[PDB]
Image (cartoon, rainbow, N blue to C red; front, side, top):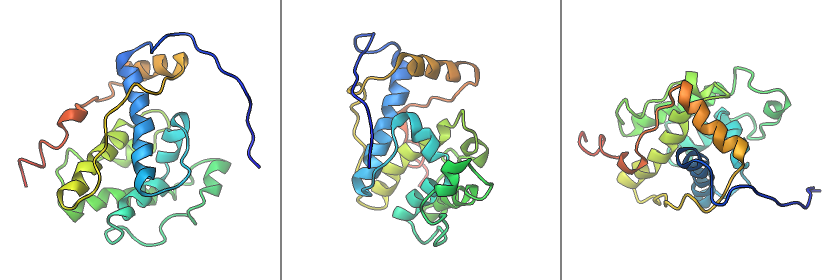
Length: 190
């Protein structure tokens, strides 16, 4: 059975940083929209990056709408048991490559062509989240898929995480594009 404790406490009022708090908050949404249509107990925000890095989620997303472009039974029994054990065995990444090919379904530009080098990095992977956000309008373009809503700022976070966020994107130079203007390239060059 499940477990847990009973505690609650905070420091700041609303948040510490705007850019950082925006990043974390975004993740909380990316999972809400994904499960909103799919329907499955997904991991938390602090572990989200740990669940997305796995190709298992890369194929599941690239198969939920385009199960053709993506091979079948690519996922490792969709259990990710061996993963939690130690981590990636240079086999899960395979599912990632497929997801990248899914773009060929419509012929998206290069701006939406994330590399595996970023997906196989348990420290930085903005192109991953960002891309997942654009996928919303993508399907909504050649289909009638739902559109992600914007309401970041309803779920607070820790001080060590938020502060660490802006930090990781202060030296590594994490490209922070405008989520408001994502479908501006593919729209021009159809």
